[PDB]
Image (cartoon, coloured by chain):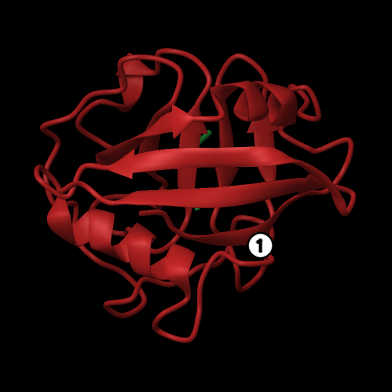
Amino acid sequence: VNPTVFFDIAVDGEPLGRVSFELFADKVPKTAENFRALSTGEKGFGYKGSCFHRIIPGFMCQGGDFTRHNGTGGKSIYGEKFEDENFILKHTGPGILSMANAGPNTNGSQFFICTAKTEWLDGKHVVFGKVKEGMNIVEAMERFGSRNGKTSKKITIADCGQLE
Amino acid sequence: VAPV
């Protein structure tokens, strides 16, 4: 029942690999649906062609700013911002897919893939998914990161959509 | 860091 979405990652335009995610629509349906629809481009806007603006090795890979490409933008399928649905799920370790935000109830399109346990983010960021396949590709993307988050090479979602 |  839980949807599966895919991202085809590219490094400086060169294909790297595919990361697939299980979206926890059972536990966080509204947040899951946002990511799913943004990955399909159903609503006319979404992640295709977007980049990962901030990659910090040993922490996380952040993306989803399809409007300004630098962390200052992004929009939800429900308007500019939506509420924190719930905090049932926690940042248990690598692979966790959670929503970025600028404070309470400020979810848009920006998300992050955890490359380590981020328990300080529990209760502040909504966890809605996890990497099902291609954690190896996330690890490969992480090596283009830096301590300040700046990427050594452009990491982009060349293609994205829904599997099955 | 995880903000916007």
Which residue is more in the foreground, A10 or A102? A10
Q: Amino acid at mark 1?
A: Ser
Which residue is more in the foreground, A12 or A122? A12
Chain A as rendered: colour: red
CA neighbours of label 1 inside 10 A, class few (<14), some (14 to 19), many (20+): some
Name the side, left or right, on which A85 lies relative to A49: left
Which residue is more in the foreground, A73 or A154? A154
SS class, disc 1:
loop
Q: Position of residue A107 (x, y in %)?
A: 33, 58
Q: Position of residue A7 (x, y in %)?
A: 57, 50
**Residue A105 is at least partly visible in this image:** no
Q: Position of residue A69 (x, y in %)?
A: 68, 63
Location of residue A131 with respect to A70 vertically, above or below = above
Give the residue number, with chain letter if any, for mark 1: A50
Q: How many marks?
A: 1
Residue at image position (14%, 55%) is: A29
Q: Position of residue A4 (x, y in %)?
A: 35, 48
Name the side, left or right, on which A34 lies relative to A151: left
Name the side, left or right, on which A84 lies relative to A72: left
Residue ranking furthest to the bottom = A44
Location of residue A163 with respect to A87 vertically, above or below = below
**Residue A113 is at least partly visible in this image:** yes
Residue at image position (88%, 41%) is: A153
Residue at image position (33%, 27%) is: A121
Give the quadrant of the C terminus of chain A: bottom left
Q: Chain ID for label 1?
A: A
Name the side, left or right, on which A37 lies relative to A40: left
Q: Quadrant of residue A82?
A: bottom left
Residue at image position (41%, 80%) is: A42
Q: Quadrant of residue A51?
A: bottom right
